[PDB]
Image (tube, rainbow, N blue to C red; front, side, top):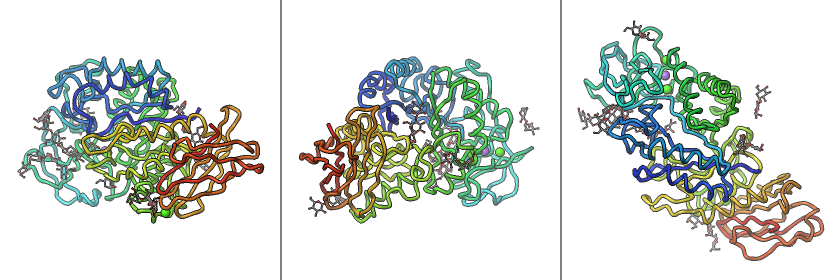
Length: 481
Ligand SMILES: OC[C@H]1O[C@H](O[C@H]2[C@H](O)[C@@H](O)[C@@H](O[C@H]3[C@H](O)[C@@H](O)[C@@H](O[C@H]4[C@H](O)[C@@H](O)[C@@H](O[C@H]5[C@H](O)[C@@H](O)[C@@H](O[C@H]6[C@H](O)[C@@H](O)[C@@H](O)O[C@@H]6CO)O[C@@H]5CO)O[C@@H]4CO)O[C@@H]3CO)O[C@@H]2CO)[C@H](O)[C@@H](O)[C@@H]1O
Ligand SMILES: OC[C@H]1O[C@H](O[C@H]2[C@H](O)[C@@H](O)[C@@H](O[C@H]3[C@H](O)[C@@H](O)[C@@H](O[C@H]4[C@H](O)[C@@H](O)[C@@H](O)O[C@@H]4CO)O[C@@H]3CO)O[C@@H]2CO)[C@H](O)[C@@H](O)[C@@H]1O
Ligand SMILES: OC[C@H]1O[C@H](O[C@H]2[C@H](O)[C@@H](O)[C@@H](O[C@H]3[C@H](O)[C@@H](O)[C@@H](O)O[C@@H]3CO)O[C@@H]2CO)[C@H](O)[C@@H](O)[C@@H]1O
Ligand SMILES: OC[C@H]1O[C@H](O[C@H]2[C@H](O)[C@@H](O)[C@@H](O[C@H]3[C@H](O)[C@@H](O)[C@@H](O)O[C@@H]3CO)O[C@@H]2CO)[C@H](O)[C@@H](O)[C@@H]1O
Ligand SMILES: OC[C@H]1O[C@H](O[C@H]2[C@H](O)[C@@H](O)[C@@H](O)O[C@@H]2CO)[C@H](O)[C@@H](O)[C@@H]1O
Ligand SMILES: OC[C@H]1O[C@H](O[C@H]2[C@H](O)[C@@H](O)[C@@H](O)O[C@@H]2CO)[C@H](O)[C@@H](O)[C@@H]1O
Ligand SMILES: OC[C@H]1O[C@H](O)[C@H](O)[C@@H](O)[C@@H]1O
Ligand SMILES: [Ca+2]
Ligand SMILES: [Ca+2]
Ligand SMILES: [Ca+2]
Ligand code: NA
């Protein structure tokens, strides 16, 4: 019953064009482990074959056309992708496709465009007069032609770029000039106006652009049979556009598509504003929680575990939070590196997987490892927690975040799941024990640690209380197994 999604990729995967095939054959295994939804990496053609996908070149080329020196994407061909999707569907797993609509990179050619430079620290401040630059804004898709779509992109479909091919200057941001040209609003306010991020910034003020992206959203959904989306860089995209794009896609397909947006800012207030402005029609990744987990793992036991959920989306708006431990941007060497230390990772996953609030996600990099950076596969430690979520994490939740090192919570279970109920206890410091209430109807039951970290048993007393124990810097999940 409890749903769990998985980000099925990491940044440093090999460019072997065999990832779709890997996902294909891993489908039954994932379902058996408790995974109910899979977020697949960008499926379209990037600026090159080894692009992770965020250097989005052609959203209609899913590894089908000869463009950018390759037919397949880094992950494989369109047919292999479709085969992977079918495999997931046949195993009862929902599919969420990534969505990049903030920018387009790898333009086919440059164009001469009128523009003014703006302050990188305050994009609302123009720092030069108007002049002509050579920008990478032309997209004709020579390898695809008009197959699937005849829409061609030009400078007027964009708000700006960060590179003038004729002068090649560093640390510059160019805002295009022209009828109705201006940074979009509303967007995040860091740097004054955070509409611009990288590559050629799409202008959400252009009617043709809005219409085209909405149409692509539907094509994309119907072509792959997607059940939902993971929306990239939303703090840089006009808020109302994203809100209405999701509504349009849901209406056009007659499907209540699930959607999780990546609003990357360690600021609950900013995220709440985004949620209100998009009318709460979709979820968001709990970025603040990720940072709390990261900081806790770096504090050597001095993090006040009683505050692990403070300032988080899952605490404030549980229904709209997708909880994650790490992702492709927080992993080693990447842009937002803030990787939760290995010793704390099991505690982190227990915090997201065994509590009643939020929609938890498992990171491919954590589960299977990141060979290129010495990160071992942790599925052996994650699997027991996934089993706890699938069979035991049900019913009323009782919180015990009452100690700076040792915290815990219990689930009283429900009749829908046999023997359900659990008692999670963890410590970022010295080990110990804690008395916790699991329910009077559990009196006499002999519980054991599903993680295997503790080998003893805990007998629930006649009053429904158990004295649960945990080792130092570890997590134990006691259940009636
Ligand atoms: O032989 C090699 C190469 O040749 C050809 O490539 C040419 C290409 O076809 C042609 O379009 C042009 O490329 C232009 C490009 O079109 C322009 O848009 C421009 O691109 C630069 C972009 O504007 C910059 O913002 C910068 O992008 C950075 C971001 O700023 C970073 O933040 C980072 O973003 C990533 C982030 O870290 C991740 O967390 C995730 O969000 O993903 C993000 C995206 O990856 O990285 C990006 C990428 O570095 O730099 C862009 C340039 O790399 O300028 C380009 C020209 O400099 O010219 C190409 C060279 O002739 C051929 O087509 C290729 O197939 C072939 O590989
Ligand atoms: O957000 C990160 C950074 O993103 C941007 O930097 C990009 C550029 O936009 C790309 O154009 C590219 O830069 C190349 C450049 O195309 C290439 O000519 C060469 O640059 C030379 C330059 O021509 C020459 O005049 C002199 O200045 O030496 C340069 C270095 O040899 O090499 C560049 C680097 O590969 O890639 C960069 C990096 O992704 C944006 O402009 C930055 O402000 C921003 O920090
Ligand atoms: O029982 C052995 C040992 O248990 C306790 O040590 C735990 C630490 O209190 C706890 O913080 C954690 O230690 C990690 C550090 O926080 C981290 O910075 C880095 O050094 O990794 C450590 C784990 O590898 O976990 C340990 C238990 O492994 C107790 O404090 C000790 O006195 C006791 O000897
Ligand atoms: O994975 C299959 C399942 O995914 C989706 O369900 C998720 C919800 O979309 C999401 O809001 C979240 O809901 C839970 C709340 O976050 C939590 O606080 C508490 O209220 O429980 C809610 C679930 O009962 O997580 C679920 C996944 O469990 C999608 O909507 C379903 O249609 C799909 O079957
Ligand atoms: O430079 C001529 C013309 O370019 C742009 O107009 C675009 C328009 O935005 C598109 O929607 C479509 O109609 O193609 C036009 C170019 O042929 C500028 O927006 C416009 O001001 C300018 O006159
Ligand atoms: O329609 C606006 C609505 O916003 C808030 O309700 C949110 C709530 O805050 C979230 O936690 C979650 O439950 O989604 C709700 C919207 O469906 C306000 O609380 C509410 O008064 C207001 O009508
Ligand atoms: O530079 C990497 C990151 O730095 C800061 O966290 C910015 O808020 C974010 O937008 C950016 O992606
Ligand atoms: Ca605009
Ligand atoms: Ca933007
Ligand atoms: Ca502590
Ligand atoms: Na824009």
